[PDB]
Amino acid sequence: GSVQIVYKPVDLSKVTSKCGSLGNIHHKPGGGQVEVKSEKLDFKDRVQSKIGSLDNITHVPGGGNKKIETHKLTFR
Amino acid sequence: GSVQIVYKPVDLSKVTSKCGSLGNIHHKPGGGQVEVKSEKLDFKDRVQSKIGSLDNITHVPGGGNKKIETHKLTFR
Amino acid sequence: GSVQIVYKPVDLSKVTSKCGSLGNIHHKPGGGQVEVKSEKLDFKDRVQSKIGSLDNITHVPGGGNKKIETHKLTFR
Amino acid sequence: VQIVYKPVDLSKVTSKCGSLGNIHHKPGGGQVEVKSEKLDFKDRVQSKIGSLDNITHVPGGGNKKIETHKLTF
Amino acid sequence: VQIVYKPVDLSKVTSKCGSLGNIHHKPGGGQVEVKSEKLDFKDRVQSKIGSLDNITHVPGGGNKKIETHKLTF
Amino acid sequence: VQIVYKPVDLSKVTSKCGSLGNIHHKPGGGQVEVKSEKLDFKDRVQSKIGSLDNITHVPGGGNKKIETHKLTF
């Protein structure tokens, strides 16, 4: 006996958008008042400490169209 | 016996966008008032400390259209 | 007995952005007071400290696409 | 004796007045037709035929902010 | 003796007035027809045929904020 | 004796007035037709045919901000 494999995926797909306009987009976070009082701040392994700080992302793609296609074949 | 592998993936796909306009995009974070009091700040392994800081990203591609196509084959 | 691999993927895909008149864009964080008071600051292994800092990364990539492939083939 | 005077003002005072933040999508689009042998206008006539108009007036929308922070020992 | 004087103001004072935050979607769209032998307008006539109009006035919409923070020892 | 004085102002006083933030997607379309054998306009006539207009007036929109900070020992 002999072993034969014929891997022929065929893709003709479309992933599309026809947006007419993306208008006036605004992102305006405000931090307020944050206060911390102690004798010690004492951080000893892999600590993320994040006092009154802002992390901000604005992400406006004219099309965000994402195609991911993973193929595997394995023989043992 | 014998072993034969034929590997002919085909992609003809379209990943597209036809945006008419990206308009007035505003990103204006405001930090507020932040205060920390102590006798010690004492940080000892892999610590991130992030006090009143602003980290900001603005990302406006006329298209963010993304194709990822990964192939693998393995024989043992 | 014999082993053969015939690896020949075909990619005829297109990733395309067609768009507009783009991007009055305004980026402009900050303004706020940050205060830290201590007798000691003591940072000793892999510490990242940010106090009152700004990070302002800005992209306007357009007419853009992203395309990635990987093709690993292993015989053993 | 100690005095520790430290007000914090994070307030916002805002006027948002007139024609703001609207969406208008394909205004018009249909046929407007006037058929005549004559149009004849002879004193102070305003005629609008098939026109689109966004006329906006704002005499208003002012702000005043006043503060005093007097400290006397 | 110690005095700590630490007001925090987080307030927003806002006037939103006029034509705000609307959606108008395919206004018009249909046929308008006027048929005559004559249109004849002779004094102070306002005539609108098939027109769209978003006229807006705001003489108002002001804000005033006043504060005093007097401390006397 | 000690005195410490340190007001923080992070306020904003703001006017947004007239026409702002509006989308106006594809205004005007279809047809306008004004078939006549004559048009005759002869005193103070305003005639608009098939036009678009965004005329905006803002004699308002002002701001005033006052503070005083008198510390007296």
Image (cartoon, coloured by chain):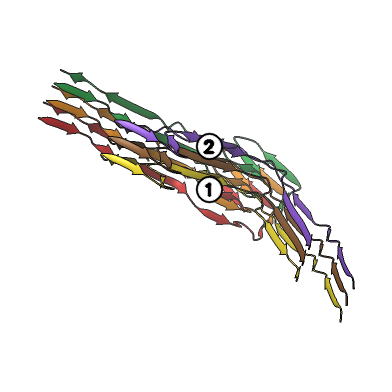
Chain colours: A yellow, B brown, C purple, D orange, E red, F green
C-alpha gap between disc 1 and disc 2: 12 Å
Which residue is located at x 16 percent, y 28 percent?
A: E71
Name the residue that disc number 2 marks.
F56
Instruction: Please name the residue shown 71% across and 62% down the image.
Output: A69
Q: What residue type is labelled 1?
A: Asn
- Which residue in the protein does label 1 denote? E54
Residue nearest the observer in this picture, C52 or A30: C52
**Element type where label 1 sits in the image:** loop
The chain carrying label 2 is F
Residue E61 image point, x, y percent: 37, 40
Chain at numbered mark 1? E
Q: How crowded is mark 1: few (under 14 residues within 10 Å), some or many (20 or more)?
A: few
Identify the image quadrant of residue B3. Answer: bottom right
- Residue at 71%, 47% in the rendered image: D38
Picture quarter containing residue C3? bottom right
Q: Residue at x 41, y 40 (%)?
A: B49
